Amino acid sequence: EGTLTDHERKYLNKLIKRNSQNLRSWDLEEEVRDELEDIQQSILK
Amino acid sequence: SLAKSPASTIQILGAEKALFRALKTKHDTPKYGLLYHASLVGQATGKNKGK
Amino acid sequence: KVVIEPHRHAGVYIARGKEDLLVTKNMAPGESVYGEKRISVEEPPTKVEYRVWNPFRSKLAAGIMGGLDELFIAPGKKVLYLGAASGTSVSHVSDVVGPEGVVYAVEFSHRPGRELISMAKKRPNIIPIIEDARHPQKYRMLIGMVDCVFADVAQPDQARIIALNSHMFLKDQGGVVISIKANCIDSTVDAETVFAREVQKLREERIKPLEQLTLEPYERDHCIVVGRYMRS
Amino acid sequence: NDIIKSGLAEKALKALILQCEENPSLKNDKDIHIIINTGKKMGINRDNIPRIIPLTKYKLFKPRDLNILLITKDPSALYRETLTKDEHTSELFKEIISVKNLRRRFKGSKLTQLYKDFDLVVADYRVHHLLPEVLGSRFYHGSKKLPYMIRMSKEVKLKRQQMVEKCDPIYVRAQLRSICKNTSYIPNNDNCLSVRVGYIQKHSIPEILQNIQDTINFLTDKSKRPQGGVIKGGIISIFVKTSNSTSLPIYQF
Amino acid sequence: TQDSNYVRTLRQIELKKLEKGAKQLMFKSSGNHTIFVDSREKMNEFTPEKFFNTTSEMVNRSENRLTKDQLAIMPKESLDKKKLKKFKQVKQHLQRETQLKQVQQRMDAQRELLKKGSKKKIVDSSGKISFKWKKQRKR
RNA sequence: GCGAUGAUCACCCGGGUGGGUACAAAUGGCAGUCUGACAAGU
RNA sequence: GAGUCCCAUAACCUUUGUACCCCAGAGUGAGAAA
RNA sequence: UUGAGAGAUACAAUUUGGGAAGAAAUUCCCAGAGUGUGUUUCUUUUGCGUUUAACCUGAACAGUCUCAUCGUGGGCAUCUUGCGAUUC
């Protein structure tokens, strides 16, 4: 109903960090993606 | 699947064990496979069977 | 164990873990239609078998990896798959719709068609229609109204094929997803120019384009156009 | 830079320079050496190949100051002709000789005469490994006249291909200038190490102290490998001495 | 002939291994994704987060862009390194395949010289040697 | 109201992990289907 | 030109499913119960 | 040192949206654009000169006979030290 209180928009938005925190573990780090990107181009070509 | 196979494969279709052993160990390969039991191959004799 | 996780679009999963792949639930467990790897995971615990979706084999899967905002294909929806060469991609579409939904697979060439029929027996929710997509009037009986129209037909006059089918069997505000191969349409000019023309032709046929996505690296010179059928 | 700040280093150098003046036996001693006691074995077999330590602040010597002997691959006609003609290297070398000629002409007592006449010996890297047989023991114990490897030209060797033989005089002069100004060391599979840091009556005490710190920084810096960063695990103690004077400590851990 | 047979068998195995492995791996998409808006103003105020209704860091994930409502035990580094290993492994299969392919071609070229016919050795300025056969029909 | 016609003699938190025997299935793996223009007669 | 003749009509490994098993084995040999 | 257009990248000033944490200002994280400068890629306009250029093809290797392949002997370690490839 779009009746979120100031507190309602805080707890839900805390969950955004919580679940997004879980996903960044799967997402893998930036440094390895630098190597993975180079390997991917060589295999794809 | 058989239709798309070349004639060489059909010759040695049933002798994969001897074929791939020989290929990897640099030895002579089989020449009859499963076709050995065809009547025409039986009529031949000596080296003519391979031909 | 592999941690299969949900995806944005219902009926699609990702077998996240070590080897992460795009994945769909198997309607007919215990067998693979084209030898794809199958993953089973216990969930409270009962194992549910899952099939891998290879983007390089299916252009629709390449759309998922690209991040298409809206897919009208979803569980419990009727889908009209034009250019269903075989069960390579239709089976996964059959997985997404689930038992409640149905998939209308349309094919013309006879040799892949016999492959399609042998797959349809395993999947009850797939209705194989062996007919030319250029004349939808022939197979009008076997097809009810369809929430989405997916087209992988690689023909120069494909936009006409979508219009005739969309005018006939697509619901108002329904789905239209088209995979475009620019080489078939015009090889002299760059792919971007060809795609612009295809979007324009769809607009003339009362299809509003929503988004467009290039399929690299999965395919070269390809893109998927997603639109909505606004008859009004 | 703590070594320079420490007064212990300055007083020892003052004592060393003074007592060389006083003691007749040390009259011929001219060079200053530092003895470094590494905590752990270096583990490098002595290859007799000098390793250059860059001294940034001060230059120990210039090529014009020293007798330089150049040993070249046979035939030496190309290298001798090119070096002797080019103005930059026309007057750089006291003598240019090939390996075969050096072996034939100089033997026995003549090798001692060659040792005295020349202050620096440089040789093509291709023929460096042959010199220990030719030059004899005298050159190859003590490290005072140990030959230095130099490269005639910037050409490189590629497998299954033949190197083009060329002599680049400016490159050879550049290498020799670096060799003279920068001090050198030789690895050995033991704690002790000796490095020249100064020359009596040429370098003031502050200059010698700076050279010592440059030596320590280069030898301890792991980033400078494989030439530098050989002294792993820190330095237990450092001394100073001439050839015949004893080790005066300048640093102790 | 047997040497040609042996190397081809090795090359065929490597090709199949490469095909199986590449299927296991997942490749991130690199393609343009345009969106169409009817109004010029809707363009100027367009924001990816608003259109996808998702967090900005969540936007950049093409494979799985999860809207906020959907948002609402192994070390990661060990998982990450092992992931790099599989990607290298498929690449090593590719490098072995090309090396075997080049080796087979040189053997086949030598075998053509053994066969009957009239051939002339032609050497280019680069030094590459090739054999050109005379235009004679085979009996 | 006994007996030589035979007495006695893995792990973890009600629940989950570990090990063993037999059979069936797998479009799961090993695993990749030989060569390519001459031969025979007068 | 060339190993059918070491069952590729097969063996082995892995996954899954079904049904049973967690005492000794040339088993021991006078105790058990009170 | 012609004109215009598109893209990428480095830098400087400045700005859009989302999130947190703060009474607001404000603080942080994330995604992003246009402006000026410099570099770079491509597309084409104009001025001038110039009219052919490259490759293939006919009976186009071989008396100082040519070439292939398998062997033998020697040189190059002061280095072509030699890949189921062609070191002399």
Image: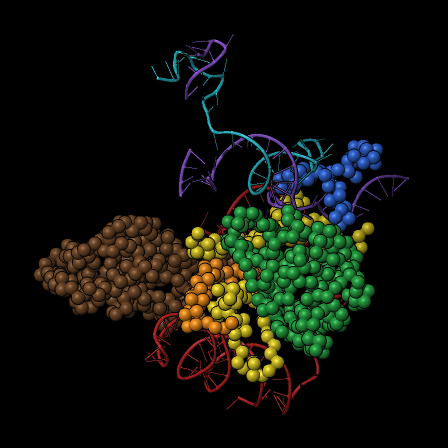
Chain colours: A orange, B blue, C green, D brown, E yellow, F purple, G cyan, H red
Across and down, in percent, residue F42 comes to 90, 39
The answer to whether B13 is drawn above or below residue A11 in the figure is above
Closer to the camera in the image, A44 or D125: A44
Q: Is residue F37 left or right of residue D113?
A: right
Q: Is residue D168 left or right of residue C125?
A: left
The answer to whether H49 is drawn above or below residue E22 in the figure is below
Across and down, in percent, residue C187 comes to 70, 72
Q: Dividing the picture into quarters, in which one does residue D199 lie?
A: bottom left
The answer to whether B10 is drawn above or below residue A17 in the figure is above
For the point 80% across and 52% down, which residue is it?
E138
Closer to the camera in the image, E70 or F3: F3
Across and down, in percent, residue D81 comes to 41, 66
For the point 62% across and 48% down, which residue is it?
E13
- Residue lying at the far left of the rendered structure: D22
For the point 37% across and 52% down, which residue is it?
D130
Residue C137 visible? The answer is: yes
Across and down, in percent, residue H85 comes to 60, 52
Work out which quarter of the rendered image holds the C terminus of chain A and state it: bottom right
